[PDB]
Length: 438
Ligand SMILES: O=C(O)c1ccc(O)cc1C(=O)O
Image (cartoon, rainbow, N blue to C red):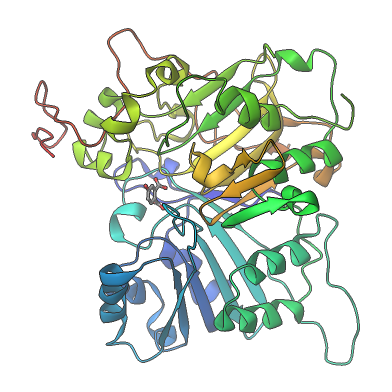
C-alpha cells in the first residue's frame, strides 16, 4: 500500500483484525530503525509506561516530551519524568484561554535516517488497549550528505510545512528538531500536513492553519466533479465543543463551507457526524469507562440539542472494531454511494472551534486556541482522480483507501442519545457488570 495508514492493535478481537495493526512497541522496535533520539508530542503521558514501550536497548536514549500542562499538572509531569535522566520536557505555550496541546506525533531519529509518526493516541496504556486509533507512518527519510545542497522537499511541501508547524512553538528544544529535519530528505512524502497552532491569523497567514488550511489545500489540489453537491461530508470524532445556538453560527457556515471546497472555481451537501451513542459505549469492550475518553459535557450538549440530529452511531465491522470505541478523528468526502472518496484526513482535531478555528473581526481573522495535527490524503498526490473505498479494512489493487469504519454511517435511532460523560447511566449495566456514576 502507498498510504501507510494503520490502526492500533485491539486486545480481544480475532487475530485477523490485528494483522497489519500496530502497537506502540512495534513502532519503536529496532526493526523500524536504530534509535538515537525521539520526541513525543502528546496531551497525556504515563512516563513509566512510555519508557517500557521502548526496546530495552533504547530506553536510555534522549526523549523529549512536548506537552501543554501548566501549574500543578506541569509539576506532576515533571515529577513523573524526574527518575529518568534522559527525559527532557518542552511546555508548549498556550497563550489563548481554554487551549490545549492535542497534537500526537513522534519524531524518531535513527542511525539510518528519520521517521515521523502522526497518530491519535495518548501515551497511556488504555489508549492502545481497546480503542480504535489511527497512525500514519512516514517513510524512512535518509540523511542528506554533508556538502550536498538539495531541498529534500516533497511535492506536497511536507518538509517546509512540518518545520513551519514546529517553528510556531518558539521552543529551543524544537529548534534542535528543526535542524534535524533540515538535514534529511523528505521528498518521498505523499501526504499534506494540516496543523493548528494557537493564535489570531489574518491576511496570508489565515491559510496556514485549521479549517482555512484544509480549504486552501482542497482548492489547490482537488478537482470539483459534476454533482459535487451530492458528495457528502463525513466527520468522525471523540469530543464536541460548544458550536453555538444553531447550525448557522459555525458548523454549517464556515466549517462545512471549508470541508465542501473542491477546486478553484466559485448548500444541500449532506453532513454525517459519527460519534458514539450511549449504547455504543455501554456494550463496548471497555464498557462505560470508555466514556472517560469521550469528553462531551452535559453543560455543552444542553445548549446545542440541534446538533444531535446530525449524529450517527459508531460502527466498524469492516475492521472488526465496532466494540472498540473511537479515539481516532477522521474527515472525508465520499461519493453519493460511498464507493469512492475525494480525500481523507486523519487528525487529532475534534469537532470544535478551538481545534479548527473560528473567524473573528468581521471575517478577517481566524482564531485558534489549540495545537492539532493531521495528514491529508489527496488523490492527486497519488496520480489518481479519486480513491476507491476498501470494502474490508484488512482484506487483499493497492490503490483503494482503507476507511476504518462502515459506510454509509447509521443514523441514531429514536431511543439513542450521544455519549455525555458527566451524567449517570444506571438503567443497564456495561460489559463488565457496572453502571456509570460520575
Ligand atoms: O485525547 C486528547 O488529546 C483529548 C484531550 C482533552 C479533550 O477534552 C479531548 C481529547 C480527545 O482527543 O478526545
